[PDB]
Amino acid sequence: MSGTLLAFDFGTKSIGVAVGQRITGTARPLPAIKAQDGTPDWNIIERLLKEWQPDEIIVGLPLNMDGTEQPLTARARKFANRIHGRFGVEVKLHDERLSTVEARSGLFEQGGYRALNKGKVDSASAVIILESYFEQGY
Image (cartoon, rainbow, N blue to C red; front, side):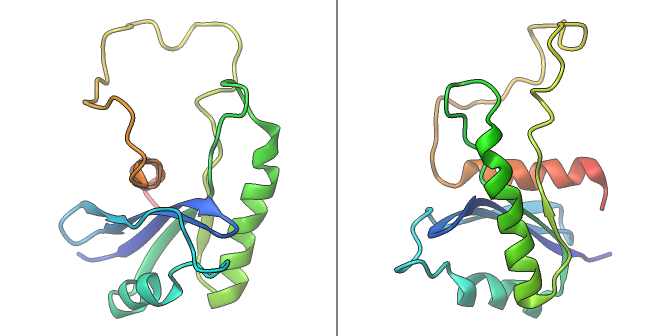
């Protein structure tokens, strides 16, 4: 089975992304969120997107402004609508569903789902956006 899919964490003039390959089940990291004068690496991703057939794409930059939910992402979701009409690819915007309910009747076991990480900024949120699509099975 094979289905190369992509996942980016970014927006205007910013490139922090993860590339996912559904051939072995791994996600490669895409360079740091710095596009050229507003030009995202379109030659870099497109080369790995079409050469391997883009099975699925997840795009959007989730950033906390005050630490909690952030209504500013509304501009992020629309960004996903841009890369879509640009190449005509099936892109999906990642929504912050982890922060929706107020009560605490879900995450009860404070110990679990551990993950070695202190604070990396190497487009890890994208491979996280990427790891999010694996949960949607799309």
